[PDB]
Length: 176
Length: 175
Image 1 (cartoon, rainbow over the protein chains, first blue to last red):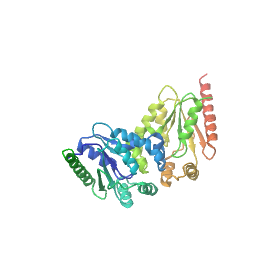
Image 2 (cartoon, chains in turn red, purple):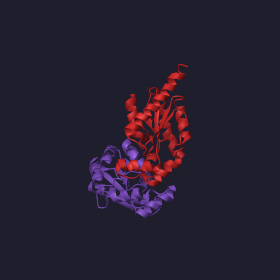
Image 3 (tube, rainbow over the protein chains, first blue to last red):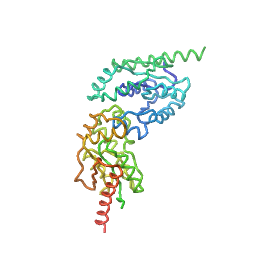
Image 4 (cartoon, helix red, strand yellow):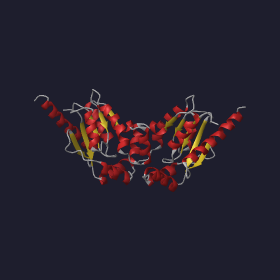
């Protein structure tokens, strides 16, 4: 099928949210929005310096993410959405209608993939902090988890299959 | 004495361009533009990952910086402007009317300043690559250099004193 609602592709920095998010969006005929582009100036400066963001820094960004997810027509947005707080809020912007695709891997695989993809290693401090901040979403509602230690085309096919199952469940409750 | 034109506060990441840029803007009654806010989505993702930007990545951003500098009314914009290529292009947006405030310091002073300010150390690799990319602007036209190993209020006063000198020189070539 095809999930009848907005999709957030989450996961730590460097996990591939934008690549996966764009492929998902194209496959579903939905527009893709890169979450990074909605950070206020202050946040970008910190990221530019390689300094971690605080909860306070994120909230106005998450608010802007939430507003995009609230549109009528479905949208696919890349957003790390590391904490449970962040995801629960985002869900309120589209109650019972928001799906999350969780891209995940160990520090080693994540680091290797970035180097294998850009020729550069992400600073170890950045990646570890992301991982310590990450609160595993598995178990939470309408969440599809996909490991990244596989071809990109496989990661996308699997994310879409997971979304198709979520769609199946909706078409079921909607028709008792 | 205000410099009659736009001002770019340059220098590597963490040098304090935004703090100084905002102070200068207030002092001159000019609006301040945070250069970082004009990076296209692709650039922000790389910075978020702690990955350096390439020359190709920067030009779209530099074009947007140039467009803001081109307005008729003077603006103060924070922009690292590390290479001479970048600065020369930005000058073209405001022919003979652009001033640069170069904030600089050694790697250790820069690193400690950031820790002292945010409780965090900038990743060493990021700071080293910035400094490696930095092409010293001293000697280029209408450029005021200021070392950061001193109080912020002193950095600002000195930047403005330097801009006042540039203004004085224009007021001379003009009359």
